[PDB]
Image (cartoon, rainbow, N blue to C red):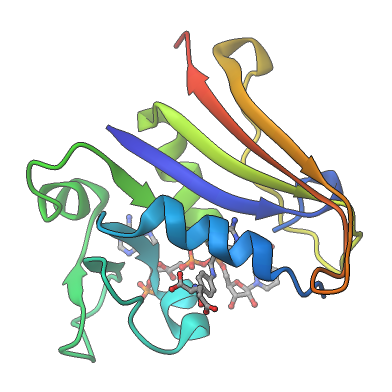
Length: 155
Ligand SMILES: NC(=O)c1ccc[n+]([C@@H]2O[C@H](COP(=O)([O-])OP(=O)(O)OC[C@H]3O[C@@H](n4cnc5c(N)ncnc54)[C@H](OP(=O)(O)O)[C@@H]3O)[C@@H](O)[C@H]2O)c1
Ligand SMILES: Nc1nc(=O)c2c([nH]1)NCC(CNc1ccc(C(=O)N[C@@H](CCC(=O)O)C(=O)O)cc1)=N2
């Protein structure tokens, strides 16, 4: 199955220091393939350890430490037969994979940020919330945040 995982500021914009959210990201992606667009790959700056890193780009790859693919269908195929594929962004990539996804792992962060790019719109009635957990800010985490998992119920 295909899952998307994202951190969402106010208004679902995709500034804080949230080690707890990065731990959540790692726990939910470790030992799974991760699919990302080239801009997200460049931003991360190094492969995510313990995961197969699959990078979408229209152009030939430029780093032998990760696997490069040129289309959504190739990216999925390159994951093989695994129980769960994690799509880690960015916007362009989330838009393409959302219709194919069965799960969303979202962190709703209580912060407004400088950006006009939003997590894709999706029908609220297509999804069921199956987990949520709110945390206030503390000495290590600059803002309050809420983890959520949603499972798809309809197309
Ligand atoms: N969207 C906005 O409103 C906005 C506003 C300001 C700045 N930005 C900038 O946009 C960038 C992030 O955009 P993002 O989050 O959407 O990027 P992303 O998903 O991380 O990466 C997009 C890149 O992934 C590749 N890709 C995606 N789908 C593909 C497909 N089906 N086949 C082949 N390649 C595919 C392309 O790489 P190739 O280019 O190598 O083909 C594409 O340019 C940042 O640099 C940010 O500063 C965006
Ligand atoms: N919940 C969530 N939070 C994010 O920050 C996030 C997300 N989802 N989905 C995609 C994404 C894209 N950017 C990034 C940037 C850095 C790491 C990263 O460094 N992860 C480490 C965490 C451990 C650490 O660095 O202290 C990892 O091994 O996963 C991951 C994704 N970021």
